[PDB]
Amino acid sequence: GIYTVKIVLNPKTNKGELTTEAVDAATALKNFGAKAQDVGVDGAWTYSDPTKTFPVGYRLIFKVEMPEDRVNDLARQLRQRDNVSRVEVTRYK
Image 1 (cartoon, one colour):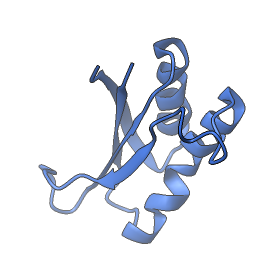
Image 2 (cartoon, helix red, strand yellow; image 1 turned 90 degrees about the horizontal axis):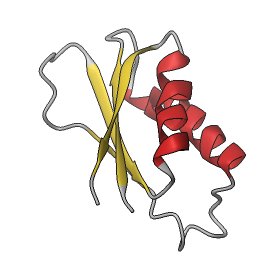
Image 3 (cartoon, helix red, strand yellow; image 1 turned 90 degrees about the vertical axis):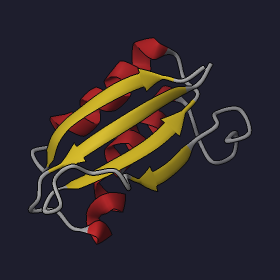
Image 4 (cartoon, helix red, strand yellow; image 1 turned 30 degrees about the horizontal axis):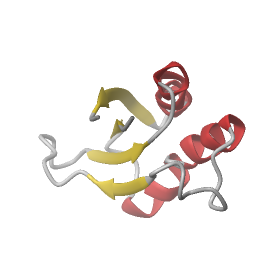
């Protein structure tokens, strides 16, 4: 299946920190067992949110293919960080 993770970041963050904020998901995935070596299995894709509603705020969206049970924790580890406003998961496939 395919799951999508939508990050909402504090306005105090930077576009250069989008890689230091998502790294909690990189570590979450790393802990889940998803690596670049088997990225052919886990269809990961990271991109910024073009449809933000707060110009001053930041939003970062990326897709994975992991069990929902740990995609909720994928998001949990992200939103856990104080820099992050909130992270919500939406199932795609």
